[PDB]
Image: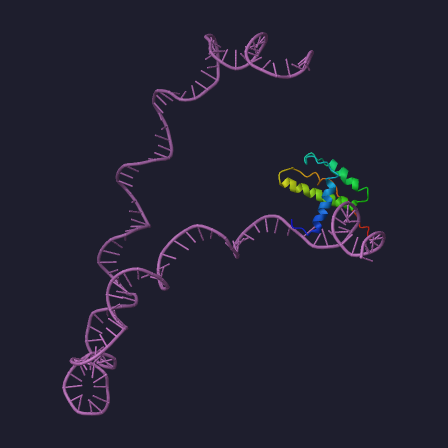
Length: 89
DNA sequence: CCGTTTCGCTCAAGTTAGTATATTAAAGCTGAACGAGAAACGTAAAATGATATAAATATCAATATATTAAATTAGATTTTGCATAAAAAACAGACTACATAATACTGTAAAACACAACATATGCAGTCACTATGCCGAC
């Protein structure tokens, strides 16, 4: 997709967290519940900004999957995105 | 001179900062296959350079005089560019006459199938054998 080096690393850092927080079961078997169970698990730890990037990266991963004949719908576009206000003074 | 500890670096996982596009519409680029006329080449044949010497023929000045090709006219005429207009033939604008399809209407056989009482092979209904290791039992 022609990225600017660093940006690519950011994605990999978000993908490595998904495979460790979500089973390696079929995509169609992945319900919306098990996606919010892991998501909210990082929202209570104060990592609100992290949950926003993880869901945005994971959601886009399925859009490409649907395009290549794998799944019919994205069960990630149903969950809410955690808002995060800047705490930096 | 060498060892030990601090510091410059990069990998790994959180915390923020920034900018915003998809289709129409019509080209523009470039690798690869497609299709004739004119001149430089080349072997072969025809014209010419090679070559020389006494005898034959041309080289040329300076001026008188008869001769003639041919540009320079100058008047004569076919040739050439351009229509004008009517005789003669082509061809729509009419029309009845004639043979021909779409249609108007009568005349008649027969295709296509329901309906109904039988007739019966054949698939389905019900039970045992064919064919060969399981399971269970010993090794």
